[PDB]
Amino acid sequence: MNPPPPETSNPNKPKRQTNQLQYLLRVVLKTLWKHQFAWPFQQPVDAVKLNLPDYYKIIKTPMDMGTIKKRLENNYYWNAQECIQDFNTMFTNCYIYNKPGDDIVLMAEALEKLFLQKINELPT
Ligand SMILES: Cc1cc(C)cc(Nc2nccc(-c3c(-c4ccc(Br)cc4)ncn3C3CCNCC3)n2)c1
């Protein structure tokens, strides 16, 4: 089975809006979402549909851009670092599960390069 997806809305977790988190949603998430290579990263890895029975034995901190979109939209994060950590966790999961030069890794690396370029322009 797949696990349930990561939590995206927590009534008990405090919320706030910052210009960095607005940038992470309206610039960073939006730009990566529209990238040609984004499709494997737009939702949790469906290990059932993809026949990857070891995926969630190896990856115990799953992350994906559909979850990050929901966390941003729901004001789930208190600070930008929490959202940047989620993007980094998602790329790292892909790297750990696969091998250098695999198609999925080249795709993740291109998205990560674009992510880092956008993060360099994160406002104050
Ligand atoms: C035929 C084919 C070929 C390719 C390149 C992609 C897909 N679709 C697809 N969808 C979702 C997840 C993956 C995937 C990930 C992965 C993606 C996001 C995160 Br976060 C973490 C890991 N790691 C490997 N894979 C594939 C690699 C090739 N087949 C076995 C599974 N792949 C399908």
Image: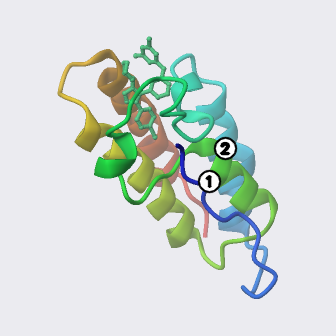
Residue behind label 2 places its C-beta within 8 angstroms of ligand 1:
no
Disc 2 to disc 1, C-alpha distance: 10 Å
Quarter occupied by residue 16: bottom right
Hey, what amino acid is under mark 2? Answer: Gly
- Residue drawn at x 56%, y 58% is 122
* Residue 70 horizontal side relative to residue 101, left or right: right
Q: Secondary structure at mark 1?
A: loop
Q: Secondary structure at mark 2?
A: helix
**Residue nearest the viewer, comparing 80 with 94:** 94
The answer to whether residue 115 is above or below residue 35 is below
Residue 74: horizontal and vertical position, in percent?
81, 64
The answer to whether residue 27 is above or below residue 22 is above
The answer to whether residue 100 is above or below residue 17 is above
Q: Determine crowd level at label 2: few under 14, some 14-19, many 20+ residues with C-alpha closer than 10 A.
A: some
Disc sitting over residue 5 in the figure: 1
- Residue drawn at x 61%, y 70% is 124
* Residue 2 horizontal side relative to residue 95, left or right: right
- Which quarter of the rendered image does ligand 1 occupy? top left
Residue 101: horizontal and vertical position, in percent?
20, 19
Q: What residue is pinned by disc 2? A: 66
Q: Residue furthest front?
A: 1
Hey, what amino acid is under mark 1? Answer: Pro
Tell me if label 2 and label 1 are in contact, CB under 8 Å.
yes
Residue 80: horizontal and vertical position, in percent?
58, 69
